[PDB]
Length: 279
Ligand SMILES: [Ca+2]
Ligand SMILES: [Ca+2]
Image 1 (cartoon, rainbow, N blue to C red):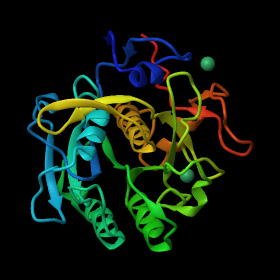
Image 2 (image 1 turned 45 degrees about the horizontal axis):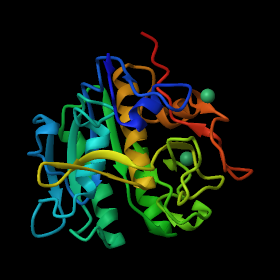
Image 3 (image 1 turned 180 degrees about the vertical axis):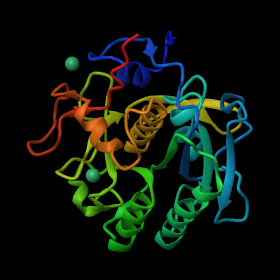
Image 4 (image 1 turned 135 degrees about the vertical axis):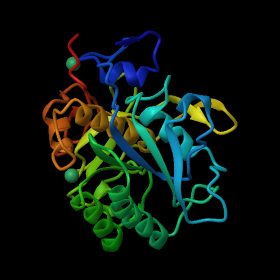
């Protein structure tokens, strides 16, 4: 399948080179996989989700995404026009408030929730969790992300937007999950992206068009935008049977575009998520 005039990030993950405009992807599109978006929620009614999104848990008064961030990330995972895995199922877990903030204990609870809740869902091609969030280092947040990964969920987490070493941020610093840095459409590390030995992979993160609340769309930037590219690609590759939740991050790194990025500090991987799609 080919989506013409796609958002640059979708084009980038299906090309060995920057500057293309078509998103080439296998039509299975993540069907049969499930991605939990742990964030401000998901506006499931957005026409771009086509019925495939639902809220499953909130830690606040409403399940409504009153911010847009979680809707945007969910759209990059799996919306029709803006998504990597256009046929995946999306489950929203609202651990962040409508200002985009959330206490670590609530974020931990939401990770534990996904580890259990997945056992009640029919996700035959496997389960992914996209965590476009984080703050300062916390061993308990890291442990929660490690548990979620251990339970059988492919966990993708943002590296953080501090232009600093991700070792000081969580859950970015948890080794066992897939920590995602951000790049721009010219294949530079995004100016804000964290870096460091713990990063596993980079994804498109600067000027990412996706769904927004109110049935709208907008472009925003962050490692929060790169993370759902990788979560969606994992779902896509799991549906293709090329990898599993336990091994998807390593598979994505070993099939990434290598050395294409600039302003990567020595000791940080130079790997850009790539679907390797061949018609
Ligand atoms: Ca290249
Ligand atoms: Ca890792």
